[PDB]
Length: 51
Image (cartoon, rainbow, N blue to C red):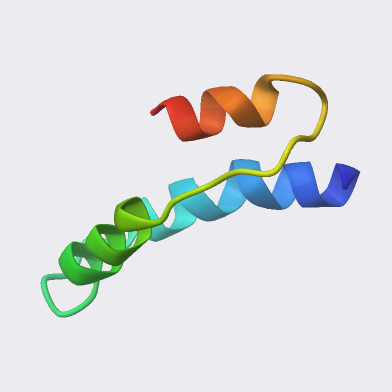
């Protein structure tokens, strides 16, 4: 869950950095339709899903 918190802190930024119409639009659409972050280091991951 600690490396998992690190992976949460990474993955959202990593997918949002890749800005391609072929990919980014639909991928973040389908993400935000069901986006979720599992608890790790308290509310830090809670901030992750807050933005």
